[PDB]
Amino acid sequence: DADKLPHTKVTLVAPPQVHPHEQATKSGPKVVEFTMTIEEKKMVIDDKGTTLQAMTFNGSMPGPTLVVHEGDYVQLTLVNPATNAMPHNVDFHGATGALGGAKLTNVNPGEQATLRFKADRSGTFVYHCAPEGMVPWHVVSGMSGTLMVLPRDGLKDPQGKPLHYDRAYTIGEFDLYIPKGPDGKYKDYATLAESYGDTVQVMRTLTPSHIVFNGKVGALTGADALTAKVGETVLLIHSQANRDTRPHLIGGHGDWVWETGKFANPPQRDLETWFIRGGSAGAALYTFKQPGVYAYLNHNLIEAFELGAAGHIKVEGKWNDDLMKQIKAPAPI
Amino acid sequence: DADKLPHTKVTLVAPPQVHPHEQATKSGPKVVEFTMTIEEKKMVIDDKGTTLQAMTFNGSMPGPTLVVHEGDYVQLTLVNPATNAMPHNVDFHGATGALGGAKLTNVNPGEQATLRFKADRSGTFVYHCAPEGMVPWHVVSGMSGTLMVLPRDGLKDPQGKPLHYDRAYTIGEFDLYIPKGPDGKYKDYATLAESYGDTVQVMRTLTPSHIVFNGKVGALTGADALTAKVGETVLLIHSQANRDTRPHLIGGHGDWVWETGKFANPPQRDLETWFIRGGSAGAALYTFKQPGVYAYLNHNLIEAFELGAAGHIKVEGKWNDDLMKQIKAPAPI
Amino acid sequence: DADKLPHTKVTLVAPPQVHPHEQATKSGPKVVEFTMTIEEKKMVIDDKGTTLQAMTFNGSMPGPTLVVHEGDYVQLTLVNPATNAMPHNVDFHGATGALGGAKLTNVNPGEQATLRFKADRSGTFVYHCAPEGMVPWHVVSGMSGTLMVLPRDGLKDPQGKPLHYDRAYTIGEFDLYIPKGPDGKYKDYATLAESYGDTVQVMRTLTPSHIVFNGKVGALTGADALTAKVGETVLLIHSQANRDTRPHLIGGHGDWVWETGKFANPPQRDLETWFIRGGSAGAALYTFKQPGVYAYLNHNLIEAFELGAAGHIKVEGKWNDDLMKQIKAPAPI
Ligand SMILES: [Cu+2]
Ligand SMILES: [Cu+2]
Ligand SMILES: [Cu+2]
Ligand SMILES: [Cu+2]
Ligand SMILES: [Cu+2]
Ligand SMILES: [Cu+2]
């Protein structure tokens, strides 16, 4: 049975952190139990006060990252409080059958349901809400996150060597379609339902008004930067459930990258910029060699700097003059 | 000679089916003869009656898939009836020299021409019309399809193991640019030529009005779904001659995928969502493990659910409770 | 030291040519010195007289390609004449640390600075201007080019065999955002600074007005075609610092392609159409087998034929009838 196996509970943590877990494991399959509560709310998504009638898993954008090993069974309890207004569900791209779980988790406000599925394929996978007749709206409103399924003996390079990371960070990139008035000012709506008709008009143009990391412009900049040390190896998980993106680290590289996100395939190395297909999650490894501030962004630079898709990584350590050196500071010709 | 070799004729079949053929073959090179007749017509492309002044190879969108083995010679007779109004030609991406065949097949209404080219490279390749001064228009109006060139000893995995499919289905994804009036209603034109000027204005915005599989919204849904059985392996051929797309199977995966479409390269596995570059055809293999209805779509979900790029696969068989199981149906908290 | 090593100077050449260099080298690391002067100017970017208030490295779009071997140190002297109006800098994606060099090269009009960085990773890399608060504008105005870092023992295939090229050509693809008036005519500005506000409005739509190869519509067509001979192998370097593109050679293929551009990874073969992620440079090898005119373009065909992203290659040699042959010229049915 797929049931009899040990059952364990995981306590989910908010982006950009990832809950504690082991990379390689000497241990057999288990049933990992997770709980997620849906939360509809109006959020401030920029520095000028623009608002979004948003829909979330666990109150954040993106939803939390769930991590298990290849072979485990995922047991998710999805709860939809009576304070919400819309029906919701989940679609795990890492699962097999019934529209990824969506058919078995239709949950109206005040209901809950429990689904179990075998995670028999390795990689980072997107999960998202997908209620019949309104999938694009719930996804674009914030309902997505990642499931990471690690190979039981950890991540490997192309020749089979072991690859380790010291920390993992999870970034969700969201293309947002906030309507504008005649003024040229973004609209504010009193209820979620009221935002609907205008939002679908903007969606159909295919031109986002804002593209943000983790829920807002500047979520991961300045004081909210990601942090690391030179010599530390970081796993950067990047998901985009609806639209393509092309991540890049200014002053760094993707040492080892799975741009399609599936760990059974060999990774590519030394990438300047990688590509995550809308509807998927990818992963990149990097080891910091120089201290200082780094920017992590979508390298359509108008999308990064005008629309919002950019973040910071602040790195501690000692400068290395052999890698890079200013021989002549700026001066008069 | 490349001529002396046996000559054989193939009878072309309409999408989404593919004409009978062998995967591995113990047999030498041959000259495969195919005939295609161009057909200009006005087609209904949605469920609300919107019309398109369309241009086709053999009366369908996409044109039929032609399948040969690596080493064969393709011998195509292109016919352009006197009832059409425009000159046409063909450009095979699988061919070498003279703009892919386009320079040797310029055929005015009432003319025909015969081209022969060696298919010396393995994979799925796009073919499309390409008349000087109006290529984008003929392509966007429906003139494209796929040529599949199989390795003589069939498809293989990365370690060289044999890979087989039970059935093959061919999907053509078309980005359409139908002008709108002041009303906000799509225009209807009496002739093909009359549609031209407005259509090029819409094309230049780069925003399609509709994105459809095989000629219309709902072509492959409900009663027109693709069909399969659990334990059956299907080859899903996907072409897009002008614009990128990112195919995904809800509740399934791409077991083995050639997203750039060329069989001499190793395939990737366990993909949630793959990517077909505009101007190319890719291929994915999957084996059904669970019965039920599956959706096959472009995972920019606004493109799939608002603009039309989505289809269904209806699968017969027995549920497998170990893969997925509802432990607690929806109920009150 | 990284200094003590021999120092050598390279004389930069204009696109589409690449300065003389060796592929494999039996020689150790050196310090290669290069000099680039920034040049702001108004350029004519089409055949109808449209103008662009452009910004360049060395007076061309794209900037010149710099080529070194893996292990060398790049020593760039960046000069910004007193005749320019804006501050500039450089960001090498091939470098590690301080925003790719951008923090150490901030150069106001009338200043110069010298940076040295180790090129420890193999491939074609984009370099671009990136001044704080205005990066998208300087990039989109023309400030980008490629750095090619060759493996010390040359390019290799997947099984390790040596791969050689006879000539290399460098193509920069630029998405341009030239504002339009009420008339429907493109605006002309007296100064660079005056173009700014309108340009950022057009950028935010994400819809280029023009997409060109090397600075203008028709830069590489007709009399300006690239040239080759049958039996010759060409390396086609393609960079796009802001926006995706999907290169294709009509009548040819990418024999061996590094679409993500990094030489330590195995290349893919027999590609009809490849993909360069915005923010990166890729490379493809091809050997001409048939004489005649070839087109090299972005296979979103509206982008290629309406917006400008298309070029020509004129090939000398003898027709090969086995590859392709017209058996029946166009004639009456
Ligand atoms: Cu929902
Ligand atoms: Cu999905
Ligand atoms: Cu045609
Ligand atoms: Cu083509
Ligand atoms: Cu600049
Ligand atoms: Cu950059």
Image: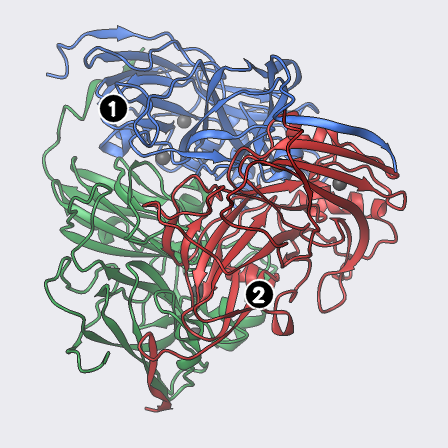
Chain colours: A green, B red, C blue
**Residue at image coords 35%, 76%:** A39
Pinpoint residue B161: horizontal percent, then vertical percent.
35, 49
Q: Quadrant of residue B309?
A: bottom right
Residue under mark 1: which chain is it in? C
Secondary structure at badge 1 equals loop
Pinpoint residue A304: horizontal percent, then vertical percent.
40, 45
From this view, report whether residue A15 is shown above or below residue C109.
Answer: below
Pinpoint residue C161: horizontal percent, then vertical percent.
32, 24
Q: Nearer the viewer, residue B175 or C231?
A: C231
Pinpoint residue B252: horizontal percent, then vertical percent.
42, 65
Tell me, yes or no, whether the two marked residues, 2 and 1, touch with CB atoms within 8 Å: no
Secondary structure at badge 2 equals strand
**Residue at image coords 26%, 73%:** A74
Residue under mark 2: which chain is it in? B
Q: Does residue C112 appear in this view?
A: no
Query: Mark 2 is on which residue type?
Result: Gly
Label 2, on which residue?
A: B311
**Residue at image coords 47%, 49%:** B275
Query: Mark 1 is on which residue type?
Result: Ala
Task: State how far apart marks 2 and 1 are (Cα).
Answer: 48 Å
Label 1, on which residue?
A: C119
Q: Nearer the viewer, residue C89 or B12?
A: B12
Q: Nearer the viewer, mark 2 or mark 1?
A: 2
